[PDB]
């Protein structure tokens, strides 16, 4: 095992769904491939400064490197891309952070980000998107976007259940569908690839339960179930209907005049929360035209994959969008962008995706005060037009900063 | 049969993939449900005026109403939503136009727009999107968007091959996948719905063939295959690879330095056309940030469904986006928006989606001169800030017009 546990840290423990976070917690981190070598050192500098400015010395994180991706073959052997040890270790230390990851081609494995998500049963991909004043945006009014995506991570088409065209197994599957199930709707059965998309009662409800609980705790105004439920009646329509049934049964929602929309009342607050639904293709237009009407969004794995990237772009956040995959027994926060090898080692890219996922991390842990400091920091740096090439390209009069230098500018504005 | 063929028209005939369009062609049209009662009369006024201003009297269309949707039950019986007669008739008269359509709930049928597409084997959904100067847009620079989507219409998840959770058939399908195929990747097998997504060699290639032929005839600069090919290796990755193989083999494309991008040379023109690919979620960001780098887009059925609505929105075109479903033996042009019953009969909505799909219609037919007139018309009306409520809501100083009045304003600016 080649991980070295810090000598002075202590482990987070989970007691009754609530975290027990010590003053010296050990947090494992995965450096990441590609530009992970640039953004990750900046996020450690900055999380470390945010806990010192905040808790004035009492709290310290003991960071612990663990491995996945190309940096793990360089450490464990040519063919070890996801060591079982990292899975045990994220479950054991309960909270962790990672940078971008390379999956090699063909060679068995799925996509390492999905493999972690699924193997560790991290069913909530929580990706909030919000505007930071100052970001170059391609949209006229990007400040209307404050949204939070709850993307179901354990099923949908992402389960990887598929077969290559013309292989024996694909043909078996199609002899099955035609002969045993009476399926006449395949246009070209020869030279045809097949994939299976599953959507289940427990899988959508644990996600929507999470989404409506997230709305109540943070006093948000609506939850939108988005779906292409009119073509995919039983995976995606069932997703809309189960989500409505969950808000009636467990949250006591009741009809708004004709319906279908339900109103769930916030028990801590009195405000009513709307549970509504939008067909998925009209949603991608609604988020650009009426973006103030939407808030928490709940969806299956593929739709959420796309909604979040569309949303991140309109607010000018391709490179600063945060992300977290959360399950019942642990969480893994991540940079949402790729590895970008062209720019690796050159200290120029924007480190704000992983830093803002460290914000989510701390907030999860309960160190709200360090986490609000990291967003005070980043709102200052961007507003001082002090920024990395990606934002400098598009801006009228800014100071170009290296990636390390931008972490310092965040510490500077706390 | 309750269709009445015009006394004076003549039928378009197809000879060697080329259309023979007489001076008096009969064109069937479907009025549409909901606001189809408002926009369709405006499109007939305007196509009729555009052929008279253009061909000064020699050419006349003989319009022929046919039926699908709610207006067909009112004509054929409570349960007749898609008369076999309309399918025979679109195939027979070769070209047709429709407004928005209602599909009832549950009661068997799929979604009538898809049922036509599929039953009539209309494999190309061609949806071009372009900015008309003057449209209220939510994006800063919407004029950079000139794109053309080629969406595969006959397969992908849209084939409707799916089973309800807990039904006997779904369980059969899962006893099959676990027991016979060795599938361990379903998270919750009980209470699970299943859908099948097929993607085939002939289906993607007839679409990409069409897309690269469309690029060469119109002198466009690139074709982008978009796909989530890294999770769906065999439906969607195969889509990327077959599309590349088609441009090497049939169009003689050759590598750009490292590749993967191929360059196909336009035989009529000398310009080189780039065939490139973008993973689908990065595409939804690339279209908002670098929109000038993309042009003709080729994709499977679900991705295209979403790309086009995202694109239509950024240029301010929710209600003016044109559409066409094209096959080898006929075409059916359509309004892309819904029925909107709230506003039906009130003459207020925007008729520019079906009118701009009539533009595509004429262009297809070869009446280029009437078709360029209809876009001269619509660029004048919008630029004279003379417009329907949807655009008047968002605009600084315009004349509000009824839907019929807006068709007149288009005739006025030809
Ligand atoms: O690999 P990938 O996946 O190809 O990510 C795509 C692109 O987005 C940009 N990008 C990725 N991560 C970023 C980050 N953290 N900060 C700024 N830009 C980032 C770069 O765009 P550009 O190359 O356009 O700067 C990069 O080539
Ligand atoms: O049914 P649908 O499907 O719900 O279409 C959605 C909405 O887009 C708008 N819409 C649909 N067709 C339109 C058209 N032809 N012109 C202008 N707006 C249109 C209306 O938006 P709004 O109700 O926002 O005007 C309509 O309620
Ligand atoms: O990079 C990958 O592993 C694909 C994942 C992806 O788009 C994501 O997590 O959003
Ligand atoms: O209205 C329908 O039939 C669904 C179709 C749809 O979004 C479309 O054709 O783009
Ligand atoms: Mg993604
Ligand atoms: Mg659509």
Image (spheres, coloured by chain):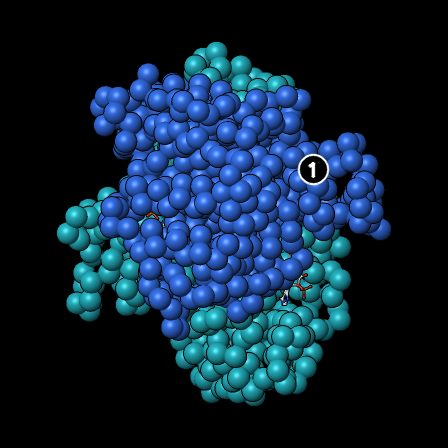
Chain colours: A blue, B cyan
Q: How crowded is mark 1: few (under 14 residues within 10 Å), some or many (20 or more)?
A: few
Q: Which residue is drawn at 66% across and 40% down?
A: A214
Instruction: Determine which residue is flagged by label 1.
Output: A213
The answer to whether residue B2 of the structure is visible from this angle is no
Given residues B358 and A350, the one toward you in this image is: A350
* Beta carbon of the mark 1 residue lies under 8 A of ligand 3: no
Q: Which residue is drawn at 43% across and 78% down?
A: B372
Given residues B219 and A303, the one toward you in this image is: A303
Q: Residue at x 54, y 58 (%)?
A: A131
Q: Is residue A135 left or right of residue B349?
A: left
Number of callouts in the render?
A: 1
Q: Residue at x 54, y 75 (%)?
A: B135
Horizontal and vertical percent for residue B300?
Answer: 42, 46
Q: Is A170 drawn above or below residue A386 in the view shown? A: above
Horizontal and vertical percent for residue B162?
Answer: 56, 31
What SS does tag 1 mark?
Answer: helix
Q: Is B220 drawn above or below residue A242 in the view shown? A: below
């Amino acid at each position: 095992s080649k991980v070295v546990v810090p000598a002075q840290g202590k482990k987070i423990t989970l007691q009754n769904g609530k975290l027990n976070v010590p003053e010296n917690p050990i947090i494992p981190y995965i450096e990441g491939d590609g530009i992970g070598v640039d953004v990750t050192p900046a996020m450690l500098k900055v999380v470390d400064a945010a806990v010192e400015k905040a808790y004035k010395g009492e709290r310290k994180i003991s960071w612990m490197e663990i491995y996945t991706g190309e940096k793990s073959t360089q450490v464990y052997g040519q063919d070890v891309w996801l060591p079982a040890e990292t899975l045990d270790l994220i479950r054991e230390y309960r909270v962790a952070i990672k940078g971008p990851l390379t999956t090699p081609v063909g060679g068995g494995i799925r996509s390492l980000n999905v493999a972690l998500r699924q193997e560790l049963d991290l069913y909530i991909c929580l990706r909030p998107v919000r505007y930071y004043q100052g970001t170059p945006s391609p949209v006229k009014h990007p400040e209307l976007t404050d949204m939070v995506i709850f993307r179901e991570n354990s099923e949908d088409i992402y389960a990887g259940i598929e077969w290559k065209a013309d292989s024996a197994d694909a043909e078996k599957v199609i002899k099955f569908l035609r002969e045993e199930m009476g399926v006449k709707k395949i246009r070209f059965p020869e030279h045809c690839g097949i994939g299976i998309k599953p959507c289940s009662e427990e899988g959508t409800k644990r996600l929507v339960r999470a989404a409506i609980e997230y709305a109540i705790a943070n006093d948000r105004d609506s939850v939108t179930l988005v779906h292409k439920g009119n073509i995919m009646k039983f995976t995606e329509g069932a997703f809309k209907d189960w989500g409505y049934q969950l808000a009636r049964e467990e949250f006591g929602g009741e009809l708004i005049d004709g319906g279908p929309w339900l109103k769930v009342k916030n028990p801590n607050t009195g405000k009513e929360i709307v549970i509504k639904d939008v067909i998925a293709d009209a949603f991608l237009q609604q988020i650009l035209l009426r973006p103030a009407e939407y808030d928490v969004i709940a969806c299956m794995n593929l739709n959420g994959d796309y909604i979040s990237d569309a949303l991140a772009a309109q607010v000018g956040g391709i490179g600063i969008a945060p992300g977290a995959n959360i399950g019942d027994e642990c969480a893994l926060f991540e940079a949402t962008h790729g590895t970008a090898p062209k720019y690796a080692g050159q200290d120029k890219v924007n480190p704000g995706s992983i830093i803002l996922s460290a914000e989510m991390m701390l907030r999860h842990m309960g160190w709200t005060e360090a986490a609000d400091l990291i967003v005070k920091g980043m709102e200052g740096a961007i507003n001082a037009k002090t920024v990395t090439y990606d934002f400098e390209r598009l801006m009228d009069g800014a100071k170009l900063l290296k990636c390390s230098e931008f972490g310092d500018a965040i510490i500077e504005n706390m």
